[PDB]
Image 1 (cartoon, rainbow, N blue to C red):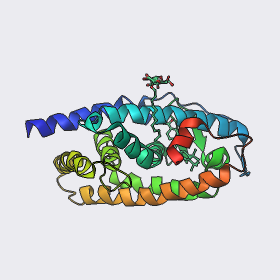
Image 2 (image 1 turned 90 degrees about the vertical axis):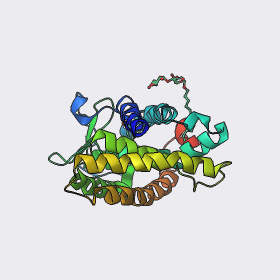
Image 3 (image 1 turned 180 degrees about the horizontal axis):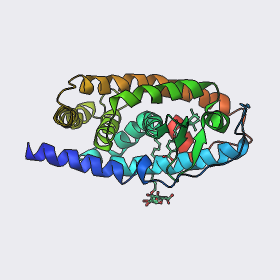
Image 4 (image 1 turned 60 degrees about the vertical axis):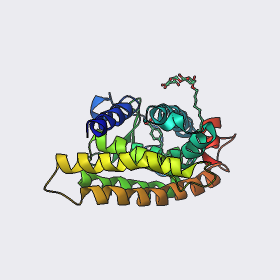
Length: 235
Ligand SMILES: CCCCCCCCCCCCO[C@H]1O[C@H](CO)[C@@H](O[C@H]2O[C@H](CO)[C@@H](O)[C@H](O)[C@H]2O)[C@H](O)[C@H]1O
Ligand SMILES: CC1(C)CCC(C)(C)c2cc(C(=O)/C=C/c3ccc(C(=O)O)cc3)ccc21
């Protein structure tokens, strides 16, 4: 129980220090391709892809602050990150959804409307991502819960080509315990919150699978290769 309490705050702090809250950010806008959907606005793609690269690095930084992660083999660390990074990217942007404005906000404050998200590369996946974001709102998750959920998504023993899946399973166990404890303590009158959060991982996997599919078609729309850390994620 003291050890579990420390795990909660280690993960929470790792999340917050690699992922500013919507409240913390100085929002700004762009007038690029703001009012009609097009196949791709390359200026929006360039900026979005640069921001995704930076957030990938931040997810690696987050991962390495999770207790036990750096005790996994370097191969397993890489395997886990490649399997989960798109999921965590999508969860991250969807936690920065402002429903009143139908916008999402990136880590530098860039705030895009739905049409600009489409035009930045989401394309035919845009409305499904926004729907996921919409359906996260009734959970009213806080940063600690988002951080713990992200950690549970990453540290999972089912990933293909893991060398030591039992070791990964044992690292996941206390994260599950921590999220249940935290979530029930915070909102004891809503006991379905923990299982609803866990089921969002499945939903997330669905949309990340579609995101990988979208990456294949986007690759045909852009004039060069995707940034190298994005290619690492997608392989
Ligand atoms: C699954 C997708 C990827 C799979 C594994 C790929 C892992 C690659 C991540 C290692 C990145 C190398 O990390 C090394 O260079 C980074 C970029 O100059 C530095 O990154 C630094 O600058 C960034 C600015 O872009 C900041 O947001 C980081 O917080 C900061 O640490 C790191 O401080 C340094 O340790
Ligand atoms: C694979 C690739 C590049 C192309 C296919 C699509 C458009 C579906 C896609 C979507 C995402 C994503 O949802 C989330 C991106 C993201 C970028 C930056 C921030 C942040 O600044 O905090 C947080 C989140 C990330 C990557 C990609």
